[PDB]
Length: 107
Length: 95
Ligand SMILES: CO[C@H]1C[C@@H]2CC[C@@H](C)[C@@](O)(O2)C(=O)C(=O)N2CCCC[C@H]2C(=O)O[C@H]([C@H](C)C[C@@H]2CC[C@@H](O)[C@H](OC)C2)CC(=O)[C@H](C)/C=C(\C)[C@@H](O)[C@@H](OC)C(=O)[C@H](C)C[C@H](C)/C=C/C=C/C=C/1C
Image 1 (cartoon, each protein chain N blue to C red):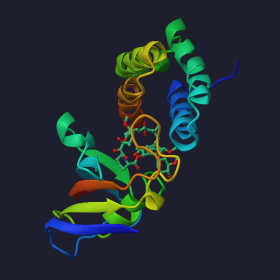
Image 2 (cartoon, chains in turn cyan, red):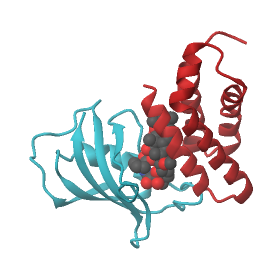
Image 3 (cartoon, chains in turn brown, yellow):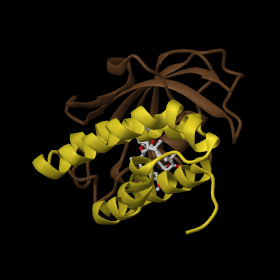
Image 4 (cartoon, rainbow over the protein chains, first blue to last red):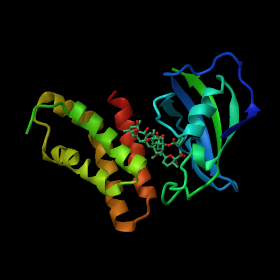
């Protein structure tokens, strides 16, 4: 599964409809808080279209739950992420990942 | 050889390359489907369309290549990502 826990709420009616572009700011870290990637360090929002299997599954189902403005922590079990194979050099096998993601805007 | 815009050529090249690396963990394949595209660039814009695209996206795609070269020398894999940051930027702009 994927676990969403509000850090800061949005309007709670403007959800990303399948096929929109989510502009978001995230910091990703491994379970222990070890940061691996953040768009906020580059000072540059990440964009992706929701539904096109463009991102990992915990993101697909996680971000679909979010409304514009909302900031959330996603706890994504390896099944809904990079699995047993990981992504070599950055995400190890089986890793439970935590994402802090804020949904800036839909386009 | 065949007629195709550098636009279409790079769009589907970048998409295929990314799927091979990210999706299949095939860093051998992604170099295969990327080296050709880079080869053309290094040879020359012939038409006006290939000229302007080169003015727009030539620099980024070049730097992306140096990052891949850097990966080849160090095995770091964060060079590959700094490369794919730049590929993503040119791809996002050419849609
Ligand atoms: C340098 O930075 C990398 C991302 C880094 C690499 C390593 C991971 C730790 C990480 O640090 O991201 C990371 O924090 C992370 O885990 N992310 C990124 C943020 C969203 C969530 C997750 C993710 O899903 O990554 C994604 C993960 C790595 C792979 C995917 C997982 C889901 C699966 O369905 C896909 O199958 C193939 C692959 C990477 C992405 O978010 C990028 C946008 C998308 C893709 C590569 C594919 O969807 C591809 O499909 C062919 C596309 O359609 C794209 C648009 C085509 C163009 C040319 C490719 C662009 C390249 C973008 C690359 C980027 C920004």
